Image (cartoon, grey):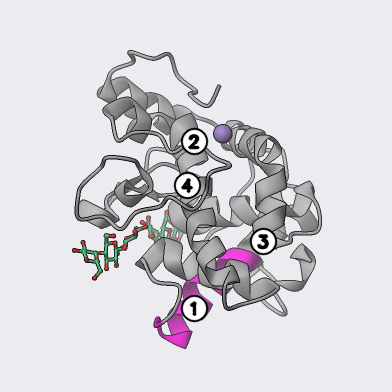
Amino acid sequence: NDGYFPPGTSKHELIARASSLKVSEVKAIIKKQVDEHWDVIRDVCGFKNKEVAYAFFFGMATRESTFRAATETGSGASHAFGPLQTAETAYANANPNYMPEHNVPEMHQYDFTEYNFYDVGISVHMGIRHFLHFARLAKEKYSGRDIARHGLMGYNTGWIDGADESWIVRYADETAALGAWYLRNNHMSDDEFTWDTDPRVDRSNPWEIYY
Ligand SMILES: OC[C@H]1O[C@@H](O[C@H]2[C@H](O)[C@@H](O)[C@H](O[C@H]3[C@H](O)[C@@H](O)[C@H](O)O[C@@H]3CO)O[C@@H]2CO)[C@H](O)[C@@H](O)[C@@H]1O
Ligand SMILES: OC[C@H]1O[C@@H](O[C@H]2[C@H](O)[C@@H](O)[C@H](O[C@H]3[C@H](O)[C@@H](O)[C@H](O)O[C@@H]3CO)O[C@@H]2CO)[C@H](O)[C@@H](O)[C@@H]1O
Ligand SMILES: [Mn+2]
């Protein structure tokens, strides 16, 4: 039951309706997916509880889209849509040159179709799956916070290793810090959001809250 909008909704309407979703509604979509997939999320990432897992994915929504669910960027393998900026590489049958993601059997891999790419519900499901693809690769060589940290580097770059430490900080550590703002300031359900570089956000020891 992953799709949010009616099957058959046009591309234009999927985008327009995503654009009009309230922040609280995007948070609810993310929570639904985290609830549905908690066991695999916990097994891969070792997050302490569902609440901090919600916050982690709110951090991703913040870093990727500033909670603007109709955000669309990139080209080819980087072409991404939705609150988590789910790339085409997440999807089954998208392009023969995309590296396969057959290591998350706990989550269905939706086919690459207009509805599956542009529906916010499918997009969020697939973003979580795509992140777990890379986090599971990271767990082969990393532990603790480094699973999620390098999983995020894979999500954004295609590669769990080899990014600059300064992008690990500006992208992955930023994501962790942004997510914690929601938990610490009672924004887990309301329409409030933070943003990349917001000076209010506490960036010290940004991973500790999750474990
Ligand atoms: O490269 C990582 C991801 O970046 C996403 O873009 C984000 C920008 O990196 C981020 O700086 C920007 O933050 C803005 C915010 O949108 C604005 O409202 C505020 O006033 O200033 C902030 C700092 O400049 O947010 C965008 C996301 O909305 C890409 O969308 C994503 O594809 C990419 O992976
Ligand atoms: O050399 C190995 C194979 O590489 C394939 O290209 C991959 C890029 O190397 C990788 O950087 C890119 O990663 C995407 C990522 O999947 C996505 O989530 C993010 O938004 O954008 C990243 C790029 O900025 O994925 C591609 C495809 O898997 C070549 O296509 C392949 O021929 C080659 O064998
Ligand atoms: Mn799902």
Task: State the residue position of label 3.
Answer: 45
Closer to us: mark 1 or mark 3?
Answer: 3
Residue lying at 41% horizontally and 41% vertically, measured from the top left: 82
| Amino acid at dot 2 | His
Q: Rounded to the nearest whole Å, what is the CA distance between mark 3 and mark 4?
A: 15 Å
| x, y percent for residue 189 | 72, 38
Do the residues under discs 2 and 3 have CB atoms within 8 angstroms? no
Give the label on residue 125, or none.
Answer: none
Instruction: Tell me how far mark 1 sits from mark 3, CA to CA.
Output: 17 Å
**Residue 59 appears at what percent x and percent y?**
59, 57
| Numbered range of the magenta stretch | 162-176
- The residue labelled by disc 2 is 108
Q: Which mark is residue 127?
A: 4
User: Could you tell me which quadrant the C terminus lies in?
Assistant: bottom right
Cβ(mark 2) to ligand 3 < 8 Å?
yes
Q: What element does badge 2 sit on?
A: loop
Q: Please tell me which of labels 2 and 4 falls first in the chain.
A: 2
Tell me the residue at 45%/19% (across/down).
5
- The location of residue 14, given as percent across then percent down, is 35, 24
Please tell me whether mark 3 sits on a helix, a strand or a loop.
helix
What's the amino acid at mark 4?
Gly
What's the CA distance linking mark 1 and mark 2?
29 Å
Taking depth in this image into account, of 20 and 5 the one nearest to the observer is: 5
Earlier sequence position, callout 1 versus callout 2: 2
